[PDB]
View 1 (cartoon, rainbow, N blue to C red):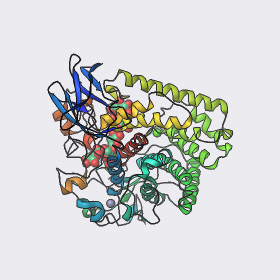
View 2: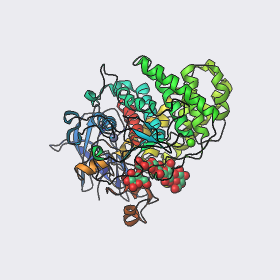
View 3: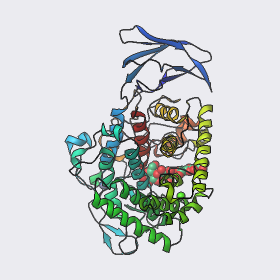
View 4: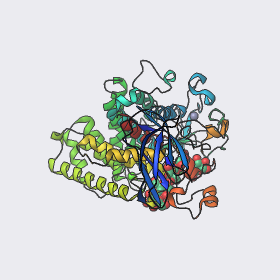
Length: 528
Ligand SMILES: OC[C@H]1O[C@@H](O[C@H]2[C@H](O)[C@@H](O)[C@H](O[C@H]3[C@H](O)[C@@H](O)[C@H](O[C@H]4[C@H](O)[C@@H](O)[C@@H](O)O[C@@H]4CO)O[C@@H]3CO)O[C@@H]2CO)[C@H](O)[C@@H](O)[C@@H]1O
Ligand SMILES: OC[C@H]1O[C@@H](O)[C@H](O)[C@@H](O)[C@@H]1O
Ligand SMILES: [Ca+2]
Ligand SMILES: [Zn+2]
């Protein structure tokens, strides 16, 4: 038996909760490290077989010993408890940089020379094309347009919403250009710059991904990976998500990098022209390409996002003719990577009210509220207070969770203020940092039970026991979609369907689009 808690820490002014498996209320105490009790209370039932202890009213910063029954845990309370972990989570993006020297003074053990520097060949042609830069998507070295757009969107949103919190962190500053932009925008620019090179100049269409034809060994260092790079065909989804992301970037970078902003604005417009002239064809891996497909049969949510993004970028009411009918569809309103309608909803809602139909706008806001109410209900019935059900624990469940937390916080910027918003955010972070049935901190390098063996090639290649820090893992996946999970996790409840093993890619991989909602949510909490 043990105490389950936020292993990174708690905010002075934030909610403070711990969990234990018990069958009745027990007293508990928080004590200074010399041992004197500073706070005492009683645990209370929350379902399954869980009790919780609330020590929110302890406001004095320090490292305390939580004791309950015969168990003890070490809990930290601090003004900005999540500053280190947010910085690590943002630095992950720079650790993923492709085609750039990462020096040892910035990147420590994981420093390396520029990787994947060769030109990629366009699929089914002899043509070559340079598209250097950007991020290795995940545990592999491929760069995929569709998930890249979500990661960029999320970082841009975190800058718009929580610039003060983000001002307190430092990326790998010396690998980026001077004069230095604010942290989120500095980091995001490297991906935006890469995305721009994935657009076909002749048509406006965007290539779906650039990868080697297959995955290299788990042991491969990035600079050792010398297989030819292949540009997979142009896709509707890539072109639409590129459009939306570039349109978002055009607005955000206006006062920071006017050349980039103007360049993104025009690229978004050329992408949208491509969408207008082409069919909504789902992407499938071409033959001889075995890397991540990032396919998606439903493409109207991507068009929605592209259209709403351009609406807000231009402020032209003309775009609302095409947006508002897409906003009426029964699409799921989610934050990607495949179901991206809520990004579009947010662009629509953050457009000047004069540019849109007031009728439609209030209906959109009403639906957003009903959605949040539904998520809030899930959270009430869950023992750890997270907006999740057992069936939500799929591949990348940590992202499912963080996107839901993100939705509550995004809504507060568009006049939909749900009372559960900040509780949900705190519970999400608590869960991510150890307040779960496995007592598992799902970020590398933090907490008392960190992730130690992520499915991540740079980590596997150097030290298989000490990985790159600040990486958020996929989390429990009840579908057991790799050999290690099938072997070791059959019959376990959904939230326990995780294993810290380097070969469990379906529960223990990492991704730029899993760090990006975590950056947003943790930034929100830091803005205390
Ligand atoms: O199965 C029932 C359940 O499915 C839900 O959709 C899930 C789906 O189950 C799952 O297979 C899929 O997993 C994706 C994952 O989202 C994606 O992040 C991951 O990305 C890989 C990539 O393919 C690799 O190239 C690489 O670089 O690593 C990354 C990170 O692991 O790939 C897998 C498989 O392609 O996720 C779906 C969600 O989009 C349904 O939503 C639900 O309704 C069903 O009940
Ligand atoms: O199914 C996709 C998975 O395949 C594995 O072989 C790769 O190592 C992972 O990077 C990838 O997520
Ligand atoms: Ca879609
Ligand atoms: Zn690379």
